[PDB]
Image (cartoon, rainbow over all chains, first blue to last red; front, side, top):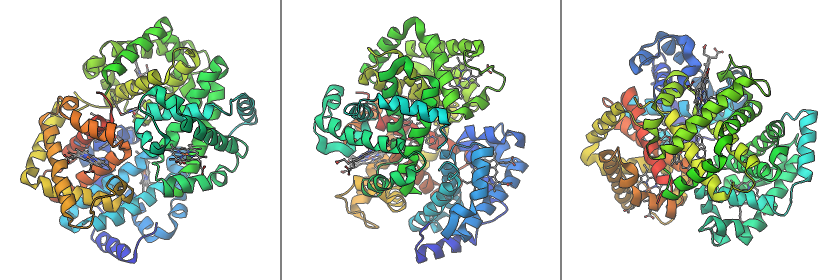
Length: 146
Length: 146
Length: 141
Length: 141
Ligand code: HEM
Ligand code: HEM
Ligand code: HEM
Ligand code: HEM
Ligand SMILES: *Cc1ccc(OC)c(OCc2ccccn2)c1
Ligand SMILES: *Cc1ccc(OC)c(OCc2ccccn2)c1
Ligand SMILES: COc1ccc(C)cc1OCc1ccccn1
Ligand SMILES: COc1ccc(C)cc1OCc1ccccn1
């Protein structure tokens, strides 16, 4: 994605403050609660019967760290998302068969989590930068069709 | 862009029977009637106030012939839809900013129109083959968005 | 949201479909399974071969649920609560699949109604199916 | 379709906005304009600079419409008919733009109401904005 030098700096600055052990699980848990049909993909994670069970589910939190990890990787290779997410793209498109519209949903839930955690610090321009970032990641994961 | 040798044949055989002067205008007209917001991009076309106005609009009909021509183009270069639609992708994405979900709508509306013209001859396998073509064209047009 | 005219169009068109509704629901399912094979993952226990009696039988159920929706077009959430429970709370069908089935049903009507599948009817039916899809993908208990 | 709990959730969270209506509405629009520039084409004549008084004025109209929709959560088509006339009949706004503004509204609520913006409430608000968007993009008059 084409981030502005200013944007790139603001994005990296905020990300450095993200709790890598919790943010991904919070975003994934919210995806499952806000867009409930997504729970179908994670039925092997156990109890996802209510919002509290989803948010408190150990496997959701553990898996969320891996998802946050992939987002960090994307942040480090904004220049070539397509190639960075090639393996994940094949997984989600061929193995998982997740409709691409869902990738955009997780990216936007992640943005809501950043806003929730950083409050006023997640300014409109900072959000605009992150929106390019997550659209890039979503676009990179949907390339197996694209 | 799959298209088993047999699907490619099926698609080719059906297209040869497609009325070049009208099918494109029926597809665009039905898009304008079924998904009314699409009318926003065609204000210079004239009266689109009622389904009869829309379906009989001479500009819609004239313009649809070009739309159908582009689909013909894709069918004639099924293995390189991205190149075939590059110019149009830039026109629709960067200049008109048409949201890409609408390319999918038009493609499916075109399928409805083919089914409407061919009846029983538009069999589920013939349709499966055309769904690949229209998904391919829409993806090709949304490419600038990649 | 359907207008008063959409409602008249839906009742009139479904009326024209008449006794063929079951057949059309079965063909819409067949078309969907062939065109978008990932939808088949929702029916692992079904015989899904062309002409399968199980698909013909399930198409009649889908058609009867739609006939019911047409008859309660003013309050579909109430009328389809059991089906919403099934698709949204139990099966968790991704809404994209409802778009696929709605499209296959419109393709089926188009192939069968060359004299009655007018642009206005097509428009009203498309919204009606978007309306049913919203109810079946929402948890509102 | 909203569950009883969704309505409860929505009225409780939005009731917290109160006199912040204008400010939050403006912030949501600014976030949208900046994050998804294609949406500015619907306001070609507006002064959209940061802090614009035009956007601040428009943002209060939008939030108060949401306030009115929350009050009439069980009867939205009737309550928002004038807004539907505007967005679906006159402006012809593409439904995708409603998802963008809805997302910017949720981002704005999350940045300001951390305690209130729980997963459950976030879910109810998202569905509510989707309900609102369906009414404003439908022609039912
Ligand atoms: C757009 C951002 C996304 C990113 C960055 C992401 C990242 C990942 C990663 C890192 C893995 C682990 C890969 C591995 O272990 O080899 C994974 C697995 C998985 N993802 Fe995603 N994902 C995305 C979106 C989604 C969405 C939207 C869905 C479903 C609605 C989904 C469903 C899955 C499933 C079910 C697995 C396998 C989990 C398991 O059972 O182990 N992902 N994803
Ligand atoms: C997926 C199928 C689509 C194809 C193949 C297609 C094809 C075309 C073609 C060939 C042109 C003529 C270009 C020229 O003469 O320079 C064009 C123009 C245009 N298309 Fe499309 N188009 C598609 C979808 C859409 C959709 C979904 C919309 C908007 C809802 C749209 C809106 C327009 C507009 C506004 C123009 C310019 C019209 C004018 O001259 O005023 N197109 N399209
Ligand atoms: C207009 C949309 C739809 C309508 C009206 C509808 C209607 C029905 C009805 C009447 C049933 C049977 C309930 C019973 O047994 O009494 C059913 C079951 C079911 N539907 Fe749907 N459905 C719709 C869309 C879909 C979609 C798009 C999917 C997924 C691709 C789906 C998956 C299922 C499954 C998996 C069952 C249970 C089948 C079984 O194992 O017996 N449905 N549906
Ligand atoms: C939750 C969804 C929305 C709400 C509740 C909402 C509500 C409103 C209201 C109350 C008006 C003000 C009319 C007045 O001055 O009295 C308005 C006008 C307008 N809205 Fe929306 N709106 C929504 C979404 C959108 C979206 C997504 C767009 C476009 C991206 C849009 C474009 C417009 C424009 C163009 C006007 C007219 C502005 C002008 O020329 O003065 N609206 N909206
Ligand atoms: C009445 C109605 C119900 C559900 C919709 O979307 C889920 C809806 O959107 C507007 C629309 C849908 C399909 C065709 C044309 N408009 C309307
Ligand atoms: C109640 C309701 C109204 C409108 C919808 O879509 C236009 C709708 O879809 C289901 C949903 C939307 C958003 C989040 C979770 N579910 C439901
Ligand atoms: C699950 O969602 C849907 C299912 C069937 C239909 C016909 C529309 C749906 O959503 C409305 C829609 C989808 C695409 C474009 C315009 N409107
Ligand atoms: C105009 O449509 C919408 C407007 C606002 C919102 C919050 C959702 C909408 O659509 C529902 C939706 C969109 C994407 C994925 C799941 N559900």
